[PDB]
Image (cartoon, coloured by chain):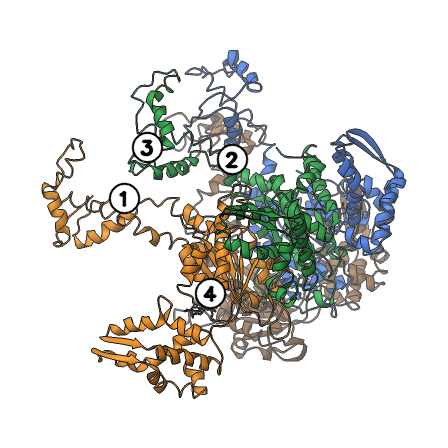
Chain colours: A green, B blue, C brown, D orange
Amino acid sequence: MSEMTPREIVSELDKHIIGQDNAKRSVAIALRNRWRRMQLNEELRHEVTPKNILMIGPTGVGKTEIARRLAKLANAPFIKVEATKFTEVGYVGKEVDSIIRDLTDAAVKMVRVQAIEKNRYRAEELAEERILDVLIPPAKNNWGQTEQQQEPSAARQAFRKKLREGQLDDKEIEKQKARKLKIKDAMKLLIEEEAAKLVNPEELKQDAIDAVEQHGIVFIDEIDKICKRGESSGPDVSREGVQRDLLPLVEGCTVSTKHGMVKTDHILFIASGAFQIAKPSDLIPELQGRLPIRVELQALTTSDFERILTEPNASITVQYKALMATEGVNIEFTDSGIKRIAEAAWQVNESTENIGARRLHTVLERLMEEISYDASDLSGQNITIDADYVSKHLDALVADEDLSRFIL
Amino acid sequence: MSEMTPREIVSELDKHIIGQDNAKRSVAIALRNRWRRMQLNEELRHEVTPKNILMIGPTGVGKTEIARRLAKLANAPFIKVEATKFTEVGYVGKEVDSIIRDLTDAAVKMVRVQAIEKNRYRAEELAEERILDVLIPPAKNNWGQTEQQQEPSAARQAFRKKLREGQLDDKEIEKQKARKLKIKDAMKLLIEEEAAKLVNPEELKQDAIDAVEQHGIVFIDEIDKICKRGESSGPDVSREGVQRDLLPLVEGCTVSTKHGMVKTDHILFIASGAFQIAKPSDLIPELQGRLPIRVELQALTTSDFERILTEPNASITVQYKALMATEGVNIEFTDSGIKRIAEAAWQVNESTENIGARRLHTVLERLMEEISYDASDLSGQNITIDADYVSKHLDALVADEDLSRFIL
Amino acid sequence: MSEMTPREIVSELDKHIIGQDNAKRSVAIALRNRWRRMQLNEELRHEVTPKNILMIGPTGVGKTEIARRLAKLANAPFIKVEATKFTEVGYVGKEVDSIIRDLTDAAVKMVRVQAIEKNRYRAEELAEERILDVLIPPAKNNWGQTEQQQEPSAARQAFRKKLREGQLDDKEIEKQKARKLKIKDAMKLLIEEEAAKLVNPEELKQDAIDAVEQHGIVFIDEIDKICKRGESSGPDVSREGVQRDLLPLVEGCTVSTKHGMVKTDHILFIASGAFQIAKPSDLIPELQGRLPIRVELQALTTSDFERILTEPNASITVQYKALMATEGVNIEFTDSGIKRIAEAAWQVNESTENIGARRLHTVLERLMEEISYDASDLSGQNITIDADYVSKHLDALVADEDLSRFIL
Amino acid sequence: MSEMTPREIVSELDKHIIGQDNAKRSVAIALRNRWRRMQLNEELRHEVTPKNILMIGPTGVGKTEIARRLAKLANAPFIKVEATKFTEVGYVGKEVDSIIRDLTDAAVKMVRVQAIEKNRYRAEELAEERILDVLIPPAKNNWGQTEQQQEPSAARQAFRKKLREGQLDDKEIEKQKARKLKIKDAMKLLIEEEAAKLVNPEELKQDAIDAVEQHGIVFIDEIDKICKRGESSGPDVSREGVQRDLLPLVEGCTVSTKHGMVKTDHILFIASGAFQIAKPSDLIPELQGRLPIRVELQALTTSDFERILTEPNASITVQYKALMATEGVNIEFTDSGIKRIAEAAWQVNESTENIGARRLHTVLERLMEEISYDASDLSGQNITIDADYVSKHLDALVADEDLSRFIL
Ligand SMILES: Nc1ncnc2c1ncn2[C@@H]1O[C@H](COP(=O)(O)OP(=O)(O)O)[C@@H](O)[C@H]1O
Ligand SMILES: Nc1ncnc2c1ncn2[C@@H]1O[C@H](COP(=O)(O)OP(=O)(O)O)[C@@H](O)[C@H]1O
Ligand SMILES: Nc1ncnc2c1ncn2[C@@H]1O[C@H](COP(=O)(O)OP(=O)(O)O)[C@@H](O)[C@H]1O
Ligand SMILES: Nc1ncnc2c1ncn2[C@@H]1O[C@H](COP(=O)(O)OP(=O)(O)O)[C@@H](O)[C@H]1O
């Protein structure tokens, strides 16, 4: 099982989300206040109430990714539903118990794929027993010693080591089979047709169910755009409603679905958004109060950037190096470009409109349009990417405001 | 069977709902005016009419939880439907006899789980007879005495006491089975595949039907916002209708459904909401008359809070201690912080807007942000949470109006 | 079969609907004009046309209950559809052939339950044959005399009389069974599992069908709010439409449904409502003319009340006595309170708004809030409820207008 | 497997999309920034993010066809969804994860047909073994040599060469068969009933899944008309939402589907449209940031046309020749008509409104009305289509503005 202490939770955070400590902090305080529970009895296993979180602040500084990530290391199943959607001011038809239904549909194509390296390496030593079986059969009547089985190997395990270097031969092996095929096929087959025997009844469900149930985490994005305070950001309280609908979810219900009936009850909720338009004080009271833990995030810096450009472990930048290396190019970003790199983000974000950390992403892939293209030429060649570089393909762009409008 | 006297019903209320005596009172007066019925004949079993309840008052002072709980000890099935919902001013598609429909779908995953420690302990002694049977068979032809049965036990009840300390052996027992498995599995199985023989035909229905039918209790929240008198709380009498739709439910009909045909006729209804917009006199007559018993509730006090902070048996505050302890921290709340604890909620509720008892929930989880976080360090350490404490992390917050607007 | 002469029909009416004679009158004249038909041939069995009724008048004086009841003694299946509904000015989706579909869904959970005391007392003498069968078996090879069967009873019918006073023993009796249970269970079982053998193929349908088909009665409430005459009570003739849709029903069609295809044709219709807004002259002509029989009702009196308070056979008042007795309380209403009781209704209904007979209901349950609560104390005690009583808990209430607004 | 280098990707473009080099370029830069990924590990296989593309420019100059084709040689599965669609301002019901859903439903009737000349020529040699088997059976007990198998052929491979010139005989061969048919049938059958044994379990899915997944490419057409800045191209931010909905798709989710559960995460997206109404800077941030790579296209020239008229490998013009030949007409276009051919499109596009390259298509099929009709007469006759020609059937048309409005 998972847990992690408060700080532990944080620290893996600072691994991919620069700054906003306060932020992290809370979310972890929610995720232990979580664990804690379990460890009680039955009374209070069921009278204490997922400490759901309200995420006030500007855009692109990481409310989402703070959640997204928290959850990945919780190893919780997770989904982010935009608040908008349930509005349909195009007037369609939106039901909110859907949300829970998709927090299962990952809670699966999550259980699945998170079962093919736990039970994959367990059955490449079971797809071999099925070819060292057709090239040379362990002659009828095994005289039980389990050590006269590694004794077929007296040539059998000479073919076992010869499966990795010489294949493409015509063979046929044992709703079963009885089929005559070929070996590089078949090798790619059995595998598949073997994960099946790696039992998938009321296990990939029931426990996938447990998934959601135990908990993930839903991040209800934008909540603020669904509540009133008049003028420009009120049509009707034909939005107020979606706060209502919502309630139950957060406030605790069962729900109908596909793989099994699910209990929202204990699910964790993380409600986002910026409120230049209203004020959290402005939710329906009901909601207001299921959002116990409130926290601010604040806009990142120039530095903050620079640092997001490199101190993220998946770093953007690196994404480059490696990507870029693949064509035979070392690439290497100075202190002093990683400086302008940011520097631009910030200047651009300040003239057009500011989209968050977001800009770096675009500013970059643009830096490289040159390199990133010609790359397969540079076969070995290496390049120095630095201020003086940067500014040559940037400055006038960033310069041209109205271009940036289009193309950054 | 249940009943309880008027006062009995009450006194279990005051167990988790401070004050509002008048409230309780009524509700209980409904819940016997209920029983009484039964005890009559056939004439008046079917000519007297569940004494439905109109819950006029402010928000977060207990209308819901008064119902909610009433029902829990009625051991009735219960659902709270928000009135809004049937409106869809986004225009979707709402049918209202849905309401009754879900009052059944808990009337079940309520009959269910409330049938697995009644009939659970009855068949842990029936899943053993199914293993003390495969380890050592009571040899062919039992010479009837029922006392040469505890006489297989001359070694059989030596394996019965040895089922609690040594398992994981490879065994196979008797749309039946004929299946070769193992014993920590199989133990977790049989149980399940045994609650089946614990007959679940026209019983887990029929009587679940009675449930609803005999009753639970539907709490139609907000009734007030579905009724007209003009200006800012009338769009059209395109809400009028919801009252209309509803009608029947309360006014007495059959409804179509999944596990069986239900009759709404005698279910109990408790219709909530505040009416600063209209006035109960403003329901359609038909309804109006179906909300016979009328009651007011009154906004809780500073004291009332203080008392909610502690005199609730699930106490908030306690939730802490015990939640908090789990990290190795005794926590203790003075009289005199529970004082400011309240003191605050009240002062905040009076400056932004007042959400009810609701605020404590929020004000608190905020007190603790410190404690609740650092907690895993305080391994043993104990803390004294008291006025002087409170005010250090509160006073300026509460101070800062416009913050509180966000973060309480 | 049913019929009843005109007056007969009336008289059972005056049993629970004080006054409005004219009203009754008609409805019965419809219900014989009904019978009459059948008694003709084939020509005129199918050229004469259910004499459907238009029920003009104020609210709460009994259009509905005049119908509701008429039908119960017709023993017709019956439903009251609000006219509103099909409007959806929230814009959903309403189809009108639904109506007929629910006039079947009772025409069932009516046929059903009206078959378990016709065939219940027929099979408690068939669930015994199944226990006096397991406690002492009628030894192999019955030597046919039918009078050596009451001759097992030479001890068998000593256990038959002993089934009513000594049970809870462990027995097992004969998609059948083969099951080992216990006797207070099983007794509650067999019954159920025996109504099944009380044949339920193409009988509980086909004749339930006959139900509707033969006839009940639909009371289309409010019809007037679905027709035009401009100003405050016309949006569009986007309501006119529902008169249209409707037509066929009343005017004669088949309809698709669940248990069987149904023919509206001969169904009886009773169309309600008050027309302060328009005038019956104001229906679509088509409708106008399927509402042959027109009748007024007029608002009830003070007396009328008083009399509804006692001369109804299910009397309200009595509802009290008996309900109230159950806790050990005789209760007894004077001439002279039953006077004020009413007196209030009337005064209240005249200040706030007047809801019909409806008020009594509420005025009362309020009278008793005192008694109705403390009742379980009065264990024997008896009380005199009379003017001087009444006015002590009423007068100021009725006084306070604006309270009454809420709580009467 | 595919890849191709940046330039390689390009050069096959310039094969059917004259000019717009910059365009191509990018797109290719995406389609390697794609490959590269794969070649990394697991960390960065799943932390780098398909480099999605924003296609700013005028209409009919190639955005679509640049994508369309890109994908064809990527041999990716592809779909272009119009942004409009999800709007329904007629108000229907649009879900957007539909988009992904259809990117699968070609990802298939693409895997399918692209599996019947790979495995088609593999089993025309397997449907013969099934007739050289009924005409002359390889007599019981094959004495294993695999060279006394081509030795049935001592008359058997005399019937194998005689299957191409003499058929229609009455034969019967081996949920199998046992059926008595005939041989030109049966030949057209077996084939089919043989692509089945060419295994189609969790292969025609799973890998079709990969398709989408590894990728095709969705081209979200017109993105611009789903975003706000006011006046004539904003109704509400009841379009805003479409951007919202979309999000996830591009921003990374699982989607439910027919042949299997798909992950959108890594698919490639290329979002089109012109922005004379807004400005790419005007997308919701979230999106904005997911359109990393930005590119412009520029309206083609007279020349560019001329060159589209011919330098396309499928050439329009050629379409003619060959289409036209089929009637017995060589046709030949001078340099100097292909000149006016273009010359015209350009002059028309500048007077009515300019639809892009689009016009040639129309201008042409009009040139020909004459030829294209009379063609079946010109049996041999050959024609010289050239300026002086062109202008005889064009000049006054192009002349007549308001005609062209109708008829080009
Ligand atoms: N504080 C930050 N530290 C690291 N990365 C960040 C930070 N803020 C934003 N980002 C990155 O830039 C984009 C913004 O993140 P996201 O969480 O979706 O923004 P927001 O929640 O603020 O709307 C993502 O690519 C995100 O991973
Ligand atoms: N007066 C009450 N007595 C005890 N707790 C209350 C009371 N009113 C509100 N609460 C608390 O705050 C929450 C609000 O109760 P609720 O019944 O949902 O309020 P309301 O009906 O007024 O909307 C509950 O969880 C409960 O603990
Ligand atoms: N004339 C009357 N005689 C007896 N009871 C009446 C009378 N009028 C109304 N009631 C009773 O008071 C309420 C009004 O009846 P209902 O038929 O639904 O009113 P309406 O049809 O006039 O809208 C019901 O409880 C009804 O049974
Ligand atoms: N610049 C281009 N190069 C070659 N053909 C083009 C070009 N632009 C448009 N066309 C032709 O006219 C049609 C329009 O191409 P399309 O990609 O659909 O234009 P757009 O994206 O600008 O809407 C295509 O069938 C193609 O033959």
Q: Is residue B191 above or below residue B1?
A: above
Return the residue at label 2.
B199
- Residue type at tag 4: Thr
Q: Is residue D192 left or right of residue C250?
A: left
Q: Which mark is residue A174?
A: 3
Q: CA distance from mark 3 to mark 2?
A: 43 Å
Can residue B351 be seen? yes
Q: Position of residue B269 (x, y in %)?
A: 68, 52
Mark 4 or 1 closer to N-term? 4
Q: Chain of mark 1?
A: D
Quarter of the picture containing the C terminus of chain C is bottom right
Helix, strand or loop at mark 4: helix
Q: Please check whether the numbered discs 2 and 4 fall on a single chain.
A: no
Disc 1/disc 3 C-alpha distance (Å)? 21 Å
What amino acid does circle 2 point to? Val
Q: Residue at x 89, y 41 (%)?
A: B387
Mark 4 → mark 1, Cα distance in angstroms: 47 Å
Dividing the picture into quadrants, the one containing residue B120 is top right
User: Is disc 2 on the same chain as disc 3?
Assistant: no
Category of crowding for the residue at label 1, using alpha-carbon neighbours closer than 10 angstroms: few (below 14), some (14–19), many (at least 20): few
Identify the mark at residue D175; answer none if there is no mark.
1
**Dot 4 and dot 1 within a common chain:** yes
Q: Of helix, strand and loop, which one carries label 1?
A: loop
Q: Is residue A67 left or right of residue D26?
A: right
Q: Nearer the viewer, mark 1 or mark 3?
A: 3
